[PDB]
Amino acid sequence: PQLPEVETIRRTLLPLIVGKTIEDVRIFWPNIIRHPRDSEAFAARMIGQTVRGLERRGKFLKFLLDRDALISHLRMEGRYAVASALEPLEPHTHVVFCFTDGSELRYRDVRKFGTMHVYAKEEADRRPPLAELGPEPLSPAFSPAVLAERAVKTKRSVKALLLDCTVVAGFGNIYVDESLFRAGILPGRPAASLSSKEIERLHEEMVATIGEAVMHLYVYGRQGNPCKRCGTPIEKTVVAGRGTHYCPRCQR
DNA sequence: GGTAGACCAG
DNA sequence: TGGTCTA
Ligand SMILES: [Zn+2]
């Protein structure tokens, strides 16, 4: 899921779990659990805690309990569902939180790529994976100035820069390619080569792209197809070890 | 600072 | 392929 999907999950999941008390935690793929390392300690500490809130940072979901926060990342195919303990689990269900009212929060993930960390609330923000996470793209903490500051200090491509989680939180491949197209910037441009005007434009399109999504595509996955703005076939190469889509005419 | 390790299965 | 951590 992308940041906008994660925000949707945050919004819709919360009322389904708030105020419920955890009675059991069942884990079928231990490797999902990253902290505490021992998945049995993970399970034991959450029992008896009540869900008090649900926040998002980047693509991370932060479940607030009584004493702890559960930090969860779905990666590409992780999904949460709330349902009855009386019904069979869906395929690829790896973690289940059982509540005292007979309902469950289920985590499914065909790729088994997602991660979970639990810490005392007051520690969550200064421990992995939230530590070092950059500002929310939709927040004033993410500004042209901040972006400019990071751009000049590096020799990497502009795409690599925007993919950097310390620069800005949860900006995925798709939104990077779309935003660069919209800003008229080639993804392979060295970040330091960007003018001040290009930085402001990029910031503006980044916010617009992610902002519109939280509420179609120009280039992502459209290789071999005409650009919607100029008709030139969209091209695909590899930049920053990633599938990279761009229009060689609109972007410079 | 930096990229190339690591995890997964359709 | 993807995202984010550790080495
Ligand atoms: Zn074009």
Image (cartoon, coloured by chain):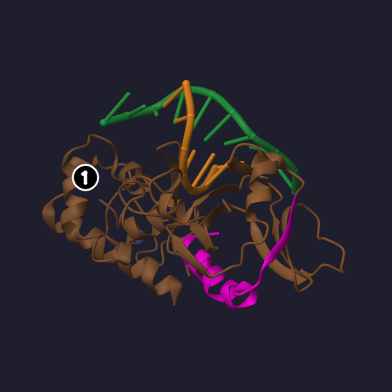
Chain colours: A brown, B green, C orange
Relative depth, front residue between A122 and A14: A122
Which contiguous range is marked in magenta? A1-26
Q: Is residue A131 above or below residue A96?
A: above
Disc 1 crowd, CA 10 A, few/some/many (<14, 14-19, 20+): some
Determine whether, in the image, residue A66 is placed left or right of residue A29.
left
Determine whether, in the image, residue A93 is placed left or right of residue A209.
right
| Residue A103 image position (x, y, % from top left) | 76, 71
User: Farthest residue in the left direction?
Assistant: A196
| The quarter of the displayed image where residue A25 is located | bottom right
* Chain to which the residue tagged by mark 1 belongs: A
| The quarter of the displayed image where residue A31 is located | top right
Q: Secondary structure at mark 1?
A: helix
Relative depth, front residue between A82 and A58: A82
Q: Residue at x 42, y 44 (%)?
A: A127
| Type of the residue with mark 1 | Arg
| Residue A83 image position (x, y, % from top left) | 76, 71
Residue annotated with mark 1: A150
Tell whether position A194 is magenta.
no
Tell whether position A15 is magenta.
yes
Q: Residue at x 46, y 56 (%)?
A: A121
| Residue A197 image position (x, y, % from top left) | 13, 58
Q: Is residue C6 above or below residue A205?
A: above
Relative depth, front residue between B6 and A243: B6
